[PDB]
Figure 1 (cartoon, one colour):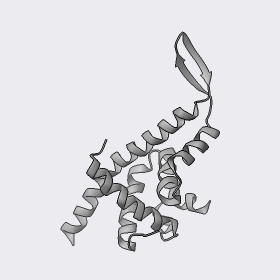
Figure 2: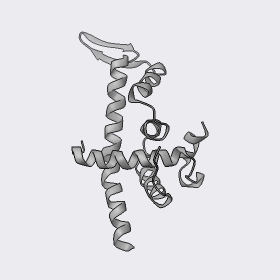
Figure 3: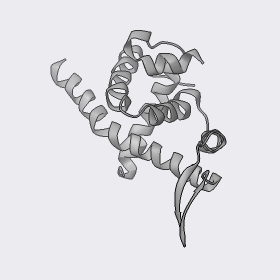
Length: 142
């Protein structure tokens, strides 16, 4: 988990970046995931939008599911509850280790809400050091 101040800082940047992405300003070549997402609010400037997009793509490409959830929340502006409702609606049957033995069952809505929150938190944790270093790298060289 990030500290409260680190979260406020990164969440702020991701809100600005998300609005910039949603306005269509990211070139398709810079991220196929973002481009595919966009085929289906104050904003940062273009230099910052590109820098953040390169950071996010370079971190989140490993987990397309989490990447999509990040884009739903920050770019489209969907609430965590709205993302979890759809996540729950399309969820696959899972092997659940219950008391007395395992069973096959689709996850509850409460479980899907917790998982969406955890996925967003884990994504911000991964993004934070890379974005912090990206801004510091730009400052150093320029």
